[PDB]
Length: 88
Figure 1 (cartoon, rainbow, N blue to C red):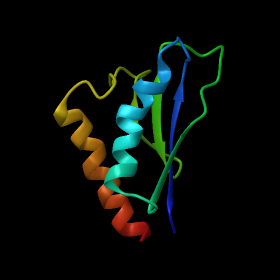
Figure 2: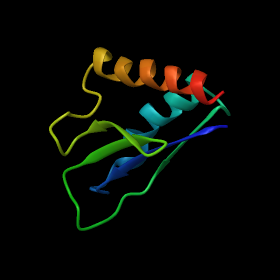
Figure 3: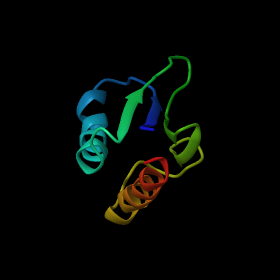
């Protein structure tokens, strides 16, 4: 199968490029083998909660940050590469 990725977020302006510079990476890395979308509910705030096939990989709400460093982005790139080669 392909694989579905998500980011739940609070739309405090600016969100499109903030998404894409991660999103337009993960799709560049793994095209057509993968999806990423975003489902940003209101009432919730201060967050960026990242999931693949119903499995959390990142939590701005638990205090994981955003992908604030190379080594933190590379966590995702490594895990999503591995999860791809399973679902393929």
